[PDB]
Image (cartoon, rainbow, N blue to C red):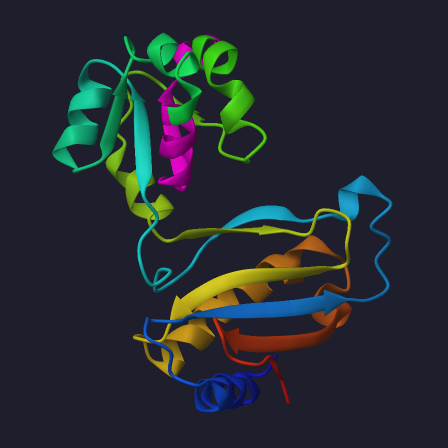
Amino acid sequence: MDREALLQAVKEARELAKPRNFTQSFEFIATLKEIDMRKPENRIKTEVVLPHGRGKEAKIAVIGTGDLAKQAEELGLTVIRKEEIEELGKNKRKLRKIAKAHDFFIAQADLMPLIGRYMGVILGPRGKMPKPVPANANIKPLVERLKKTVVINTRDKPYFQVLVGNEKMTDEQIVDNIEAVLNVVAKKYEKGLYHIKDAYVKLTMGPAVKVK
């Protein structure tokens, strides 16, 4: 909650985890108090751009045509073209694969009824419904932000768990990310961070370490 307190949790969390054979990731967990999650406005479902990214960048796919689809192959992104929509809504083994492999989907906005009608049944249950952008939009600002974005989602339990970096970034960086996440809570409720009951940090396979 104060920075050195979090530098300490981060520090300790790295210390307590047995090195396994892969780069673990850091999760931040917080439980809330005195907020009624039966009121739907009290729930959090927000996107945070983390100041230093996630560890490994979010894979983005672009559904569109024209220059939207040229800008997407110039930035190195998966392009699903207008002619493929129907072909993917009928081949659900493939579609399922594509939804597993990408974190975010951006789509030419006028194509959102087709997308909805053919891919919506797989993309919407997984929270992967595309973001619409005008057909003539500049997408590099958006692609830059989304490569560093995480979604905080409580649903109706009073707690959340977010990715904030990985074992290859510095403690200082993990705490700056964690602060970007605490700033969403600070602005959601009137009393702000008064509502954080307990905060924990933890590696992929490492025990949770309560902050303080």
Q: Is residue 98 magenta?
A: yes
Name the residue rendered at 34%, 10% in the picture.
Answer: 87
The image quarter in which residue 28 lies? bottom right
Tell me which corner region of the image, top left, top right, bottom left or bottom right, holds residue 141: top left
Query: Closest to the observer: 204 or 49?
Result: 204
Q: Main secondary structure of the magenta part?
A: helix
Residue 101 location, quadrant:
top left
- The quarter in which the N terminus is drawn is bottom right
Residue at 38% x, 8% y is 86
Left or right: residue 203 compared with residue 60: right
Residue found at x 44% / y 8%? 114
Q: Locate residue 96, reporting x and y percent.
A: 43, 30
Residue nearer the viewer, 178 or 22:
22
Percent coordinates x, y for residue 21 in the rendering = 32, 75
Judge whether 59 appears above or below 83 on screen.
Answer: below
State whether residue 58 is above or below residue 24.
above
Query: Quick one: which residue is furthest to the left in this view?
Result: 74
Q: How many marks?
A: 0
Rendered location of residue 119, percent (x, y): 46, 18
Q: Tell me the magenta residue range.
A: 94-113
Q: Position of residue 115 (x, y in %)?
A: 44, 15
Q: Residue furthest front?
A: 93
User: Residue 102 vs residue 179: left or right?
Assistant: left
The answer to which of 4 and 199 lies nearer the viewer is 199
* Residue 78 part of the magenta segment: no
Quadrant where the C terminus sits is bottom right
